Image (cartoon, rainbow over all chains, first blue to last red; front, side, top):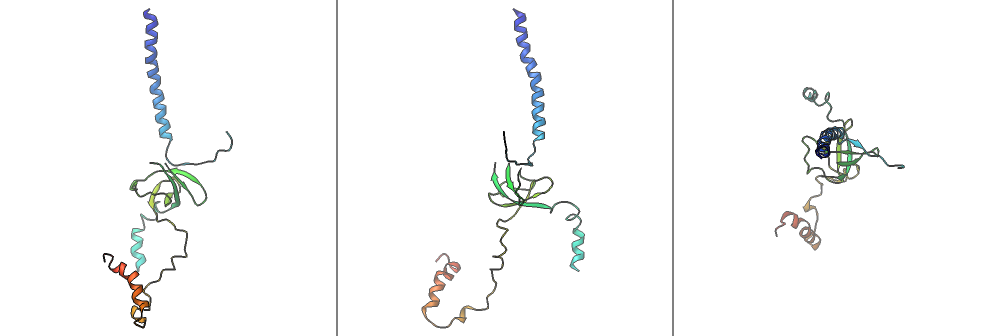
Length: 45
Length: 122
């Protein structure tokens, strides 16, 4: 009984560790986004 | 003679890159600024260091740097026409006393033109 509840409890902990990597990637995206870009016309999707 | 005094201050205003700005008219204001160049090129920029947020208005020529586009100084709009610059004269030779006669073609003009300009509170 305690084994099934221990895996689900550690699942939220492992998600928080990977969430810090996602937040660090978003900071890299925000650093990669700087106001001076250019505008283009979409041809085909 | 005047060229010698201007060469002293010409170190910061020439060697450094400030003046080489690309002037273009701003279109959309998001408070991201969409500005179309003279070469028909659209881009996105934002405010500067000393640039005030209330100075940028819709449909105004805004100079930006050619390398990394950023707002630097605003400029008065409608810079294209060169014709109306010569239409304004200065100090006409004909004076107010050159018009002869006591008739009504004088007093009627000064009351609807000169009167509201000189005494708007009347």
